[PDB]
Amino acid sequence: APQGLAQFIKVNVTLENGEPVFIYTDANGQVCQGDITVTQAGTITYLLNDQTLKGLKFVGVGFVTPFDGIIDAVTISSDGMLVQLVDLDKTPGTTKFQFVLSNTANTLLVLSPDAQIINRPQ
Amino acid sequence: APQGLAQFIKVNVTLENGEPVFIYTDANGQVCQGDITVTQAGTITYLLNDQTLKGLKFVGVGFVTPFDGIIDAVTISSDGMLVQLVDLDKTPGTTKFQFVLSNTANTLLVLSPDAQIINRPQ
Amino acid sequence: APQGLAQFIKVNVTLENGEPVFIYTDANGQVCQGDITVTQAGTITYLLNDQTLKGLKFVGVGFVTPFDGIIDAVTISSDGMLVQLVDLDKTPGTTKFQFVLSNTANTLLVLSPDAQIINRPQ
Amino acid sequence: APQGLAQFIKVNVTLENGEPVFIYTDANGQVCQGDITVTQAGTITYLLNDQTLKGLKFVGVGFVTPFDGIIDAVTISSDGMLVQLVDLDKTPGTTKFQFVLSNTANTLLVLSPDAQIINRPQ
Amino acid sequence: APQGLAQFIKVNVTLENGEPVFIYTDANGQVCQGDITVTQAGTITYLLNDQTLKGLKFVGVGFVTPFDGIIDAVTISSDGMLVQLVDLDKTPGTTKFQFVLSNTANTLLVLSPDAQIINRPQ
Amino acid sequence: APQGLAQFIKVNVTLENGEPVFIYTDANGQVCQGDITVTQAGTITYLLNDQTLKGLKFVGVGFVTPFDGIIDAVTISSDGMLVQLVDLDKTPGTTKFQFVLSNTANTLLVLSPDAQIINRPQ
């Protein structure tokens, strides 16, 4: 049976001047931008590395255009350390998303700056 | 004992071209922009009017700079129809925020475009 | 646009003889009774100051007559440190309510003695 | 091995004059008062029969004196139709409790009038 | 009014070779097997004694044949330390169940080996 | 940067003789057994196709040996329609797991029969 591709990205969050900074690293330890191109059906797994001491946990992934069909689903682990995107790469196009996190310092949700997914179907 | 001001804003969400559009109205029924100036301690109450048929519910209010002290706390009702901001208007400045909503069509979170709160202390 | 009033009350909880005692203070640090009169639309914000060492968190606000229309809605923060009442002060009358809290010592919910809200519309 | 007693009570909730009325029935279909005497270790199982059309669900059982040791624990089913009290009947005395329920009409919690448990150890 | 029987079982969980082992004890401190015979309507209360240092909490009780009517309901305490089974012992027969637990080491659920309930109605 | 493999399995659940039957299908529509061999780091995505009319939702994936390191993490979607396993395929060996589901007919959790994951590292 046909398999897709599984991509793995670490979401490192530090504090600079009291506020969160999101640094993505790839499987080689290379800093990468937030943008991903998807060229076949698959998954994108984001692992949280919270270095802020603010108790960050993923609560989901947010979209300004959530019905565009670029990302099919979001799954989250019980400890808020992992989020995964399912992308069946049927609908071509681009979508902008932001990570949504809770914190233990206050009751405000934390948003990352926007990142982009580009689908190029097969 | 000293009282603050309570502001009330309706968050009307429609669909245009399949995607959500956020229209804020004030207590007079006037369309207003998302930006609010806070000139003393108080609360801002947002009531969801979901006209999308996508089962939107508030899940919180998100901030790219959540530790800036502009908004002190966020409260949410059990049905996801109300969110309230507490703003003690001690720390002057401006912060950008986006509403975060769940939907019943898919498992992606919905984000509004950004809005601004400006604190001018007394 | 028309604004309402935002009232702020601290809910101090101590232990006397092993059991919780609720002491309300107002914005001046004055001990006040639990009763509030509402004379226009607005909000009431309750901040938990738990001095019990029993891990108290708000889980809601309870009413024996919940459909009386005196309080329109209750919102709660994610950390259980704040609850807010929305009172549009359209329907005149009085309602009795009790704070509902979880604790970390056991699986029983904690109730405050009853307090009253009196609505006097404009 | 030693067994305790399991008591079963139906919590019938109707609306009279728009507001909830709690009617307890016992295993014979007899209306009973809310008060129970516990004369050995055991459980009390409360089954919700909501006749209000307000979508009531148990969310817990509340106590003004939650650390008195009369009731050891509360368990709740996932559908909010059952709550159970564990009473090891070690500590003698009496405690007053109220059922705490959510509803689908508004975001206020619903409280029953108080009921009493009397422990008489063996 | 007619009463049933309340049974009490402690679910002791240790680690052997890095993995959980479930040891049931009865009200006398005797190790018992997981199997219970129910000969009249009643409850079975399971208390978690987690000796693993893996932060185990009950999240429910699972069944391969959940619609067989042997167990009528499951209730759980807010701290995940207690689960209770309601067994009205109307439908005779046997059912196999496993405890379902969360842990704080990872995001996998923990299952006990299967145990059996045998109903013998009156 | 290095990518893994993403596998996709549909979890079809029917009722036979009143009880759930789990039928797995692969990306070709072929019925497959529950067992999967993992030969490099990647993800396994399970999509629920509930044909039971019992309101099944995934609540997690359970393991009798949850600390064996075969599966690194489980993620779940907000609607309970998807669960995903992360398998970094570092630790070789085999583990047995069961799907854990809630239902809307009763408060018992639903377990699948066991399935196996076999890790063969690279």
Image (cartoon, coloured by chain):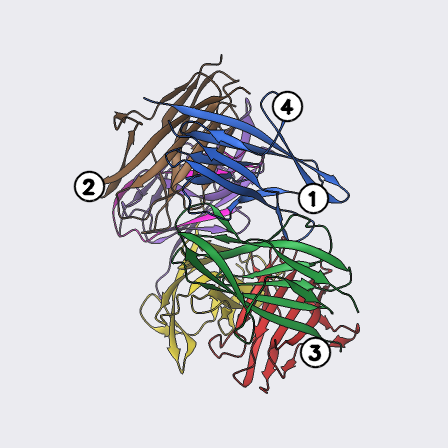
Chain colours: A purple, B brown, C blue, D green, E red, F yellow
Q: Is residue A91 magenta?
A: yes
Mark 4 neighbour class, 10 Å CA radius: few under 14, some 14 to 19, many 20 or more: few
The chain that hosts pointer 4 is C
Mark 1 neighbour class, 10 Å CA radius: few under 14, some 14 to 19, many 20 or more: some
Judging from the image, what secondary structure is the residue with disc 1 in? loop
| Disc 3 and disc 2 on one polypeptide chain | no
Judging from the image, what secondary structure is the residue with disc 2 in? loop
Mark 3 neighbour class, 10 Å CA radius: few under 14, some 14 to 19, many 20 or more: few
Q: CA distance from mark 3 to mark 2?
A: 62 Å
- The segment highlighted magenta reads A82-110
Q: CA distance from mark 1 to mark 3?
A: 36 Å
| Disc 2 and disc 4 on one polypeptide chain | no
Q: CA distance from mark 2 to mark 4?
A: 55 Å
- Point out the tag, 4 or 1, that comes first from the N-terminus: 4
Principal SS element in the magenta part?
strand
Residue occupied by mark 3: E33
Going by the image, does B73 lie left or right of E22? left
Residue occupied by mark 1: C54
| Disc 2 and disc 1 on one polypeptide chain | no
| Disc 1 and disc 3 on one polypeptide chain | no
Query: What's the amino acid at mark 1?
Result: Lys
Asked if the residues shown at circle 2 and circle 4 are in contact, with their CB atoms under 8 angstroms apart, the answer is no
Residue occupied by mark 2: B17
Q: CA distance from mark 2 to mark 1?
A: 52 Å
Percent x, y for residue E121? 58, 86
Q: Is residue A78 magenta?
A: no
The chain that hosts pointer 2 is B
